[PDB]
Image (tube, coloured by chain):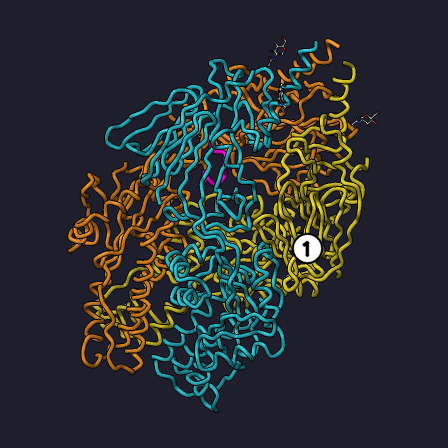
Chain colours: A orange, B yellow, C cyan
Amino acid sequence: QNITEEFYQSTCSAVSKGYLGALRTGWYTSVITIELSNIKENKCNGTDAKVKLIKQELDKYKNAVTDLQLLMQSTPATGSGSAICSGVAVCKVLHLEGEVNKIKSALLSTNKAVVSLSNGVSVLTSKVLDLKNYIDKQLLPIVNKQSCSIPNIETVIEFQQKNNRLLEITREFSVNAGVTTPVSTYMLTNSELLSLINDMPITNDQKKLMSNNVQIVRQQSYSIMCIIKEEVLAYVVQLPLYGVIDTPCWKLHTSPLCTTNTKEGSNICLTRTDRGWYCDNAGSVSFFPQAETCKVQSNRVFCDTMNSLTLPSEVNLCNVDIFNPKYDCKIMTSKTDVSSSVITSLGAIVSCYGKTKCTASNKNRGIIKTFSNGCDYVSNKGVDTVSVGNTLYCVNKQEGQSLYVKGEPIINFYDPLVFPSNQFDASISQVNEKINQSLAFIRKS
Amino acid sequence: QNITEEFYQSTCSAVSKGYLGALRTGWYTSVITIELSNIKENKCNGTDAKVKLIKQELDKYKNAVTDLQLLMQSTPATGSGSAICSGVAVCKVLHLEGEVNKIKSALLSTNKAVVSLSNGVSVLTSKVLDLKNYIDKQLLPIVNKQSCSIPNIETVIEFQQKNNRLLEITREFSVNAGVTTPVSTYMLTNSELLSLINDMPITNDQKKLMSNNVQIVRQQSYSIMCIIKEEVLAYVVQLPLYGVIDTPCWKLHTSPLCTTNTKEGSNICLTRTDRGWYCDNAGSVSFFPQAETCKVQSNRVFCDTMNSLTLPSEVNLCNVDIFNPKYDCKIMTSKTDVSSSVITSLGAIVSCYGKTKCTASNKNRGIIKTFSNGCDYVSNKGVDTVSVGNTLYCVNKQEGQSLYVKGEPIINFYDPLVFPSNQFDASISQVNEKINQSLAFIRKS
Amino acid sequence: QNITEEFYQSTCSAVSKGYLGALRTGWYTSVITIELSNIKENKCNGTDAKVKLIKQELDKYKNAVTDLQLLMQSTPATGSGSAICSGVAVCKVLHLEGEVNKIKSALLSTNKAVVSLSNGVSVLTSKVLDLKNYIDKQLLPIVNKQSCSIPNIETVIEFQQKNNRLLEITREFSVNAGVTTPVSTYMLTNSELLSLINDMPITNDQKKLMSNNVQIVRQQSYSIMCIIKEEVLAYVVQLPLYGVIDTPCWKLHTSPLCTTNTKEGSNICLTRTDRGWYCDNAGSVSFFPQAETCKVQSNRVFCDTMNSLTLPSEVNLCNVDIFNPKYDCKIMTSKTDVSSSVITSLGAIVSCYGKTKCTASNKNRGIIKTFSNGCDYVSNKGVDTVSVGNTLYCVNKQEGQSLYVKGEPIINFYDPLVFPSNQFDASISQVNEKINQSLAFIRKS
Ligand SMILES: *[C@@H]1O[C@H](CO)[C@@H](O)[C@H](O)[C@H]1NC(C)=O
Ligand SMILES: *[C@@H]1O[C@H](CO)[C@@H](O)[C@H](O)[C@H]1NC(C)=O
Ligand SMILES: *[C@@H]1O[C@H](CO)[C@@H](O)[C@H](O)[C@H]1NC(C)=O
């Protein structure tokens, strides 16, 4: 719905709320087959240019098949093995004797078919390319005689077109050791992906969600190479199942909060930690520290719980009361008052220190705001750019309401002499306990 | 001009000077159009192989158009939004009613044309592919009758060639959610990029600079998908404007500086922080901490100010006097004396500790220098490789002059017992103040 | 042989042993040539569709040649320069006058040939594409007359096929500033790579190793653009030489080890540092901290010593006795008891703290183990998944034997009040010395 933002002057941090999240909690695997032609070289005296073109493209087909064979003989392990057991188990099932013949029988008359494997998985299989029928019907009469038959020029062009998808799949599967993500249109055409979404056991609003966000679905999918066996090329496509839908999500933005003394070396800094995406999830909060783990479209966020931490919901209280005992709100400390800016969803946080020239401009009016020393904020309403030193940032012009929450910078509550300026993952209460200990070593003496 | 280097034995750091910098300070946006054919399926009884090939390639054209349509319906946000407002504003301008008709009229007779949009931007537009003219003139008479007309085989091949650039642009725009960088030759041919440079409002020496460094220009450019509307495919190419030209730049190299005691656990280490590229910029220094933010060609550096910090010019005094009060020169401390080497522009810094076998060799003479324990340096004059433990590095054979600046290692000025061995972003004066405080807790008692 | 694992309950760490390593210690360079046609535009009045198709593809050939020329005029430096001196030296040798004519003479009658350059390097050269013969024999009679001769349609298709590899090599060399890795099948076909392996001065078991792991060989190879000169396109392929073969390797996995008090803020944490791959190497241990520097296939590991550290073999004693004085076993400390899990080679380490719901399940039985608070471990025997909070990990189903080494968590030997909770690269003995100093400031008073 409405994206809103809140800047907290006291902690030099902002929270962008109103996003609807879709968290991946499951996988839906599907088998993708390509019917190949088990042919061995058939060479006869041929020299007309059309026969040469056919044998050349046919050698590129045989090399693609042998390349897929040496790729499946030794498949290198990936750091994603912890996220593909749902498809690797299917490659292991297909290696069973008689199972590849089962899917070859189910896709004998139609392109799509549900197949109950010998492990209880009712998987959906597809035959996206039929080269055994094309090579054995249109090409073999040309190459398996005493002298080779002459093909028409339309066949030469049609065979380069059909063989092309095989060659490109062999390129992607070869350079990535059998595991590719995102899933390209060569692995699965957009038409095939959308048709696979319609056949998926999900609600119509959820099919509409994945169909309206097919590129995000591709970036969160996997293509795993299985086996080439018995005139069958098989590989597993692992598509995301979003077990969490429309859950509230928010993005925390943090920036250094320093004191603004005029004598360098007498200033202390503080920055809230754990900036990133937060989503309500099953009575707790799912936190995503890495930036590429959440894809954003307008008000909607698509995250993968694979690289998340699970935090108590009280972690949100660091945004309303950071000194609050229900949650130990952590900060990092330093004496590095270097100017910077953070572009948020509806504005910009500016940490200006020293002699830095910080400003906020409108495209037609020029400079409309000059920041003084400290941490401040400006909304995108009327602001186009923000300059900090020699750097110019662009402000997101997305509609929403910003709220400037005034408050005393908490860095002012600390005596500089006893401040712990060296903490990376330290608590508010951790710093207060270190201050009680450093004040005790000087107070008693 | 002449690249020179200076190794500082006192701080285990080196500075490579003499580079001429080109910093990005602006964007030059340009609209790239592809005239499409608004056709709906026209199917008649056709079976000759040439008609089938034409309808097959025509279906791949219709799917590319519908794929671009679902890509433009929901465009996922990128982390680069802070750097593309200059082009996103044009996509927003094109969505206005009547504006796409304006550029369609300006490019009605010619390929290139300057167009004054309805927002005051005099942008340069180009028509790089004309599919409406080709489909409506060469293909529609073949498919919009009672029975389909027969095309010659040259047309089938020419249509696969023309439709190819559309299909590849749809692949790049699809997998990257509409924002690609670098800009491929499919988005913009080298001929089109060089012609776009000649038409750019810049000096002839600056056009010669971008034309001689077109790959760096591509890596620092963006291609943003706009709209497919009214037989027009439009997307914005955002090219860099280097507001800073020929500015002096230098690269700081740092390596751990430890003491060389024979009893492990009694040694302290120190490393200068903020290694990377520095450029003089508008009365201050622009620092680039990330390595991929500066592309290097011979004596020339191309940086993006988007990921830079602005520092006072006194930051250079950490290279001549690190104990100098005009700038608080920061270090990080530890007790981790692990051997390593850093390949600089004209030589190699070697930090050798413990039992590590450190050496510098010439390809034909073998080992020409054996490093003892501590931090040392060797020039590329006569040296080909440097070995530290089981690792062999290659020395850059670029011509320049190295200067070995002798000096006492500053790690020797510190009493080990009271050294702060746990600092990440700590100042020289910060460590000295912590030493005055740790000496006061034991001195009084 | 047999992959085994050992979980150390005392340190919340696991070691996966039994891997056979192949470390890169050398480079084998090879020159790859493409015979080009030195032609200038030859235009005559031509309009038959076949002549147009030929001149169109011929312009794409001329632009690929001029694009390679502006790519070789200014070649941008890469961060890999420290790993390609073995090939850059060959590009520098080829630029000598008369040397490109030497390899052009050796490959005058055959495709492959060993050439002794004028620098003592007996390099192996290959001619993978012959465009000078094809353009000058099949195309020039069509375009160098008063009126252009008419080519047959097979030639138009064959020329688009031959020119395709040139255009794709120009794309890869253009966007990557002349240095590509991995080496694609366009730079070197799998047939050409395997044939190049057979011709390499190595043992038959080592040729069998690289031939069975060609994708790992590609990912650890470089393609460097040299020169386009005198109807010759030359570029260097740098293939890895594994000077270390079948060396024992092991992977260290680490996870936070905290105390499990019921009052938050009273808990201290500890984590072993330096997780990653270790290999026995030349009397020392080669450590690889980055994850992408070692490619794994079953029991075999392929590492690059370029991004490794050399450690004494006593570093393995951190796995059997971390309090052992022969090696200073380092840890990092904090008070951040956030739950997490690490998927190992044969199981999973689980660090469960607070209210987190940690469990281990079997696909058909459901939850088979509930972890209590602390650091624990479960083998893959009977376990399919592990859930920590809202995150589900997949356990690797690889066969091997796990050993649970019981022991007291070492975090319990520390008094919380005087624990140093702020260390990043700190030693066991470092923490004990800081504890002796913090106990001395309170003990005397
Ligand atoms: C520091 O001392 C004050 C005074 O009693 C106390 O209220 C506060 O909780 C202490 N902080 C910690 C972290 O123990
Ligand atoms: C430490 O003490 C000396 C002695 O007066 C003084 O000169 C120096 O500036 C002090 N360092 C700091 C950082 O205060
Ligand atoms: C701390 O004190 C004990 C008691 O003598 C000693 O055995 C130990 O080695 C000391 N630790 C360090 C790091 O000096």
Q: In this figure, which residue is indicated by the disc labeled 1? A: B345
Expressed as whole percent of the image width and height from the top left, the position of residue A440 reads: 69, 12
Expressed as whole percent of the image width and height from the top left, the position of residue A14 reads: 57, 29
Residue nearest the observer in this picture, A187 or C298? C298
Is residue B47 depicted above or below B64 in this figure?
below
Expressed as whole percent of the image width and height from the top left, the position of residue B133 reads: 41, 68
Q: Label 1 amino acid?
A: Ser
Q: Secondary structure at mark 1?
A: loop
* Residue A404 appears anywhere in the view: no
> From which residue to which does the magenta span run?
A288-293
Q: How many marks?
A: 1
Q: Quadrant of the C terminus of chain A?
A: top right
Q: Quadrant of the N terminus of chain A?
A: top left
What residue do we see at 33% from left, 28% from top? C360
Residue nearest the observer in this picture, C421 or B105? C421
Q: Quadrant of residue C420?
A: top right
Ligand 2 within 8 Å of disc 1? The answer is: no
Q: Residue furthest bottom?
A: C146
Does B403 sit left or right of C126 as displayed? right
Does B72 sit left or right of B149 as displayed? right
* Dot 1 alpha-carbon crowd within 10 angstroms: few under 14, some 14 to 19, many 20 or more: many
